Length: 148
Length: 145
Image (cartoon, rainbow over all chains, first blue to last red; front, side, top):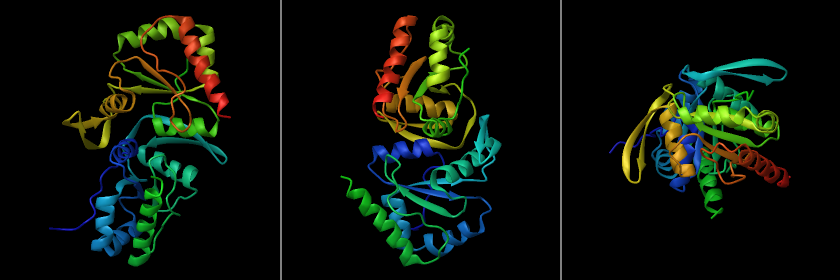
């Protein structure tokens, strides 16, 4: 018996498909290998037994590392206000999509979504308040359940 | 002639949403002879290539792509455990569970929410039928609108 959050997927498409088959909501965790505040969140909040259970049991966690160096199969040239940028790594890919889809470039950044990508709560960033985080998770969960 | 826009599903889908276009998924392979035959017999047609290049966002999903995933993924399927390790294993698997198909070439036309805009299309070298497939998908897209 050792209650700690287990990161399910790093891959968005496969995580979304698993969640869909298992009728679970998804938590997107935009994070970084060297992200100080992500790690502070992990140690101060994720280690709480109630938070850990909810994330492990009720959500499909997808950890999106914005500093992941894994090469993209081929590079992708994008236009972002207002010049060319070449996306080369998985990390570049996720930094870019966080900005264009959620209007944020910060980590930690948590987004609760349903199986069609609709947000289930407002986003949560860095805040070590355990009960506020629990409210954030339970609210998303109930908004998900109210879809069915 | 037909210029392949994206290999990456998520970035291709976001570009298509930003540009208000439907998406064509092309399940294919580097070593896929029937994919090459289909490209040579049908994509070389001026009207086909014009529709693909101007009206769709093409996403080429190579099922034999060896690029490693960030970390392997264990999957349960029908109903046995398998470990996916490369981008190609990912797209092979997703082709099966999402579209009920395991062969290439396989084409799916989808809207920006991922809803299919037509029956999918497999290997058939009929230019007219392929034009009809594309135009129908395009007509269906423009109707949600």
